[PDB]
Amino acid sequence: MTLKEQILNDIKEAMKQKDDFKRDSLRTLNAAFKQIEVDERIELDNERIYKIIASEIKKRKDAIELYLKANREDLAQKEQNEISLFEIYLPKQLSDEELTLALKQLIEELGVSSLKEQGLVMKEAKIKLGASVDGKRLNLALKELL
């Protein structure tokens, strides 16, 4: 069962269990999927789905902060509740020890040797590892190795 099928199945379940918030949030996610599929004439693999989710979460993290500056705790919580629903679909995250071996391997593949190449390693690691590690952890582990 595909990731798209998984999300559509959760929309149906939300409808049958009368959880309107879950229905509406996941339909928002599915609307984003179909827009990219139509605009780009592609089929979504899990990797592209992760990027779509990550971008929708990042936008909401940004909104939560503007809402708090606007004294609207209600709005921030709602956006945060949306993130919790979207995060469920993200892949297993690499452990600290797994992240280290992966970076050591990739650093040898690139021939890097110093922090002056960290920007190059950051971009390449985000491609090779994808949604299995976030930027912050990747940044912190690169500093320790280079």
Image (cartoon, rainbow, N blue to C red):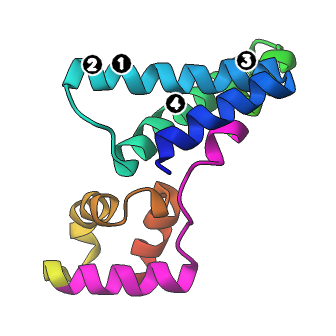
Q: In the rendered image, which quarter is residue 40 located in?
A: top left
Instruction: Please tell me whether mark 2 or mark 4 is closer to you in this view.
Output: 2
Q: Residues within 10 Å of mark 1 (few under 14, many from 20)?
A: few
Tag 1 residue: 35
Instruction: Please tell me whether mark 2 or mark 3 is closer to you in this view.
Output: 2
CB contact under 8 Å: marks 2 and 4 = no
Tag 2 residue: 38
Dot 3 or dot 4: first in sequence order is 4
Residue 112: % across, % down: 18, 79
CB contact under 8 Å: marks 1 and 4 = no
Dot 1 or dot 3: first in sequence order is 1
Residue 103: % across, % down: 35, 79
The secondary element bearing badge 2 is classed as helix
| Rendered-image quadrant of the C terminus | bottom left
The secondary element bearing badge 4 is classed as helix
Residue 93 located left or right of residue 111:
right
Relative height, residue 21 to residue 130 (above, below)? above
Stretch in magenta: 84-108
- State the CA–CA distance, disc 1 to disc 3: 27 Å
- State the CA–CA distance, disc 3 to disc 4: 16 Å
In depth, the one of 52 and 41 nearer the eye is: 41
Tag 4 residue: 56
Dot 2 or dot 3: first in sequence order is 2
Residue 94 in the magenta stretch? The answer is: yes
CB contact under 8 Å: marks 2 and 1 = yes
Instruction: Look at label 4 and name its amino acid.
Output: Glu
The residue located at (73%, 17%) in the rendering is 67
The secondary element bearing badge 3 is classed as helix
